Length: 302
Ligand SMILES: COc1cc2c(Nc3ccc(Sc4nccn4C)c(Cl)c3)c(C#N)cnc2cc1OCCCN(C)CCO
Image (cartoon, rainbow, N blue to C red):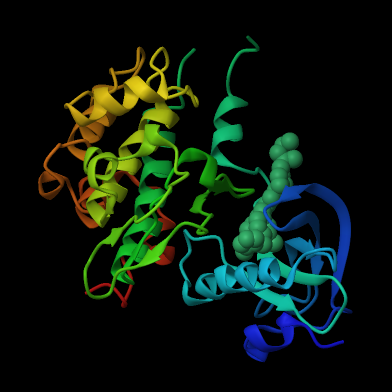
């Protein structure tokens, strides 16, 4: 049967519904239900791969479907070791399938919460630098390809079986080749606690604002996923941040990681570090594998 899937996805991202086997439910997803499972011959040199599978059911408007596909279409553009990668979509069938790289340990937020005692030290500075570095790497790729994530936060990063952290959710990211910015016209649903002052004020999003968010996820990592500006309301956070407010250094936070935050929170966007700069300052503290797999140390980067 002919559906949006047939036109809106290059058949060069297609894979036979027979190659894809679903096992158990992982959870709800933006446009359908996500399943863990296996995808034969989708990864070069793998006879089999573990993957996450999303199912869009007939019971979803064509509008719904089209947008959903277009969102995935941007994914396609990205090929970075620290971005969750799209493995392909099954388009000739009754429930459209999207096949993503499996991240066995789920979202960085939940993962961080799992480290707490049971209703409060943070990971070791070394574990933390690795996360910070792997997140910064993905973002630097994003920015090199002229995108603004807009929605960077612990809840949007995934953690792989080997504890590698990757950027994961791009429903909110925009193209910025020419302009180097995105301006929000109407109502926005982005959480205010991750938003840069300039973004709260004008609706402007740049890579400088991404770096601001990055600081906040460093803060989330440090506090094992506390709510930023706890004790303030969205109202007060708004006011507080725009007028120069800053998150307090976590109790138990190694100075270094909080210095890094304080630079990502420079009020003047132009005074913040680039994702490349950030990586540079800690690249010598990253587990060996990094050099091989990172975008920082890749050909694309120069
Ligand atoms: C918890 O649910 C999970 C969702 C995942 C996921 N999500 C996902 C999101 C969107 C799509 S399709 C889509 N919709 C909009 C855009 N796109 C591409 C797909 Cl296919 C998967 C992707 C990925 N990616 C990769 N890995 C995942 C692992 C999950 O859990 C296993 C461990 C949890 N665990 C049990 C923790 C301990 O309890």
